[PDB]
Image 1 (cartoon, one colour):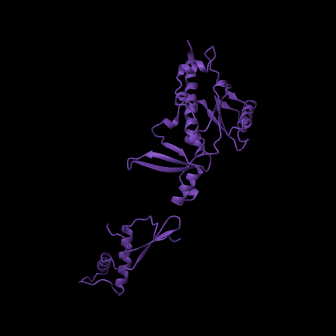
Image 2 (tube, rainbow over the protein chains, first blue to last red; image 1 turned 60 degrees about the vertical axis):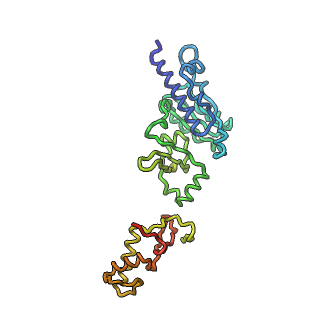
Image 3 (cartoon, rainbow over the protein chains, first blue to last red; image 1 turned 45 degrees about the horizontal axis):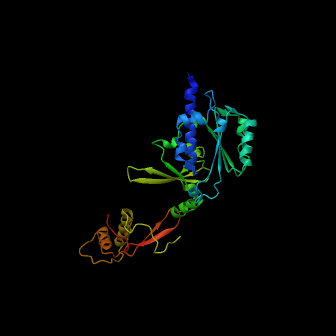
Length: 215
Length: 84
């Protein structure tokens, strides 16, 4: 008898996979093996003797791949954080906003449970150039990019971006747009001004490639 | 803003529109007693003549296809491949 907690562990596990996959798509070195970490190994490698999972230890660091660095040089390491506190507070986030800033982490992903205090929320933009992202577990229990309707989105380098505008001879304002808080942009941690090549299937031609600039 | 005769990416083919306006402008001049460059083998209708000039490639006109960015390419009617 494990009631709710049983199917509650499975959600933290699933979301953990989405975070691994997400980080990998951004361009960080991660074993396909780690992504496919079976539930049982999770319950062991990350849970205490009582059935309850200890999010504090799930947190990890992510490093840019050799391949990723060849295009995006300024891509520093990344830090993921799973807060054991359901509702995060200003005192709780501060410790995080500092951890990143301290270890000179370029990007910090804060994965919380139910929500965060509006007070704490206004603690994110405060350590440039390092940026901090927030994700509600629920929104990660499923990888949206694994959905039929969601095509392949690829962050373009400022180089490609320049190349893109040069050939089609376009102003930035003439390119199709994509919202900053767009689920996929949030997924690839897109920043305003960045372009994404969207490779979609077409019933007209084979493939069709479109572009969207993050607003 | 001008584009060298080389490096032209635009179609070698004439567009139905280009042809339509060329047959229209040229016919206007023929109807106004302007000189004809093709041997009039009977034809009297201006447009019918304009068309004969297009086929025999004797229309001294140039189409300035502008690109959305402001630049433009210059194609001569003679040059344009007509097949519509």
